Length: 288
Ligand SMILES: [Cl-]
Ligand SMILES: [Mg+2]
Image 1 (tube, rainbow, N blue to C red):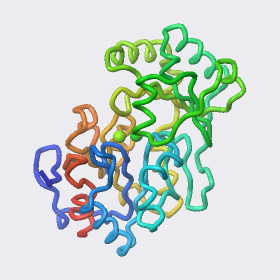
Image 2 (image 1 turned 180 degrees about the horizontal axis):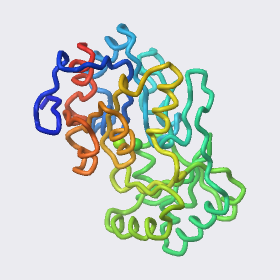
Image 3 (image 1 turned 60 degrees about the vertical axis):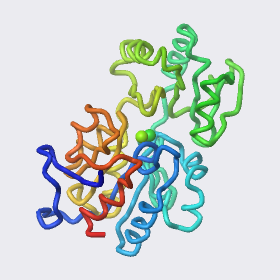
Image 4 (image 1 turned 30 degrees about the vertical axis):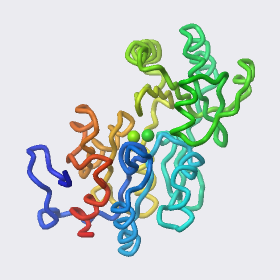
């Protein structure tokens, strides 16, 4: 499966498009990266041609820039994928090309502690990874924290419970067991509606971050930087934390592996992340 189709299942054709796509925003895990957390050669080959044609490709991830650099560092070192500008921590940390934070949305400290106390009260504090600007922290290590470290490719430093109060954080990620994902998700959303964003971003990850921030806020700021109209931008993703940027832009692609809620928010449905998604996006929308 290597096609991109609209809501009616009709293939998108370049000659039918009246908008030049100048910039592509793409999620990392589950979108650009395959199940092996690698950039396929087909994708890599298309990204090279994109640079040649001056098409900007921007990462839009819940990850920090640091963990991203650890996963695709080889591609960054060869200047084949730029991390700046980039949208990180679900928009809460969005950088321009100068590494300046055009969005810097820290979590309120009272809310931080309330989330923390709540997590301990329901015993998911052990699964919590707290994100500062430069470092991540946890309170213990278990099979679920282990599972997080392996995929994230950047280990949190272990700290005591009392230390969280002194930290300035942007988000918390709960690497939960699959057997308490659904219920824990209800409790967080019930407890913290109109207080903080709650999203099941990847596998059994539950991320909490600034209520009025998301990836699409990052998209708007970066498009504004380069004087690019949103109509000349394209977003692609697979997760709940991509919904805002997929529905916010006229041109957006939900990869096949995405859920139905995610696909419905996107303008188009494309190949899975294991099927060289961005390669085909670049073909259809930018003519290679
Ligand atoms: Cl993500
Ligand atoms: Mg994803």
